[PDB]
Image (cartoon, rainbow over all chains, first blue to last red; front, side, top):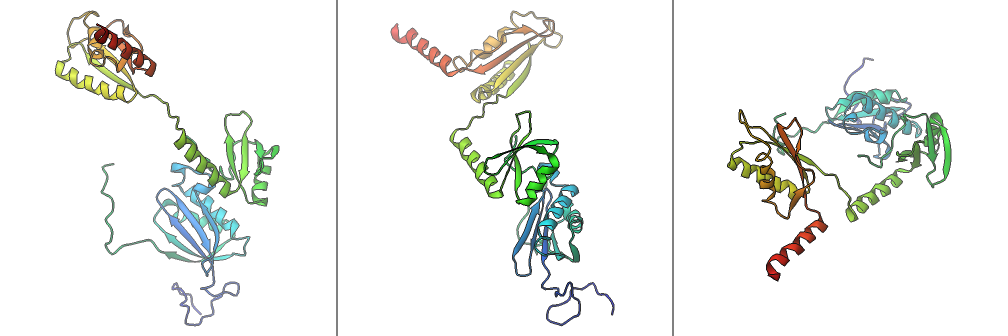
Length: 137
Length: 191
């Protein structure tokens, strides 16, 4: 058949399998690309924490955490703790427009994990709370 | 400014005096051999003592790194020891108006009150001829406003071939203060 970019809905039965697992069963890699940090947490389909890594936990400080090299390092460190638990395929759910938004995804690929999907879950309000005032710098 | 946090898997120095999680002295080992023990037991290394010339690093669990700084958060609260002294500077002119001298003399009282060091410099007024007799009479005129609170640390000197005078003030020390107090009472009460 062809190849669709839309995720396979759980209910309807499909033939897309990864190591004999359905899309729902694949573990999830939650990436939080902030402006000054990048936190990564790998969980299973049943919301069981498997691995956690961040630029701060890798020995970076202050303005070194808001770089693409620190996000990649945290991806390699989270792809090494989850690869010991039997993780190969993951579903990325990136949250934020930070520097380590795509660099952490590369680090996960440099750790032995195969990405099957990229989900964006950046918090967007339909006006809710008022942000801080603009700055003069 | 440091924090009791893990250094990571990137070590700058080849040779480290590694320490066990339980406090055992593993002994100096190559940089590569340090990371092998971080994976074998899933532990993070923290630099305990930077000052020593031989590098000292201790490998401990994440929970152990939380209890440590949780105690440095209480010891400093219980017995805080922040003693750095800020240095403030003022550059006056011989012909400075009194109104500006009362505004700048009230600023020195806020600094002195904050245990700061106030370096005051006086320069020859714009196309004004003046000696060091009345040019040094502004310090005594400023110090008089703070009789007991302030005292000289340094004394007027010819910093720039005499065209300028520099002095430094400080908040009166506790002991000195008590001495001043004692003297004040005798002059009026004993009389």
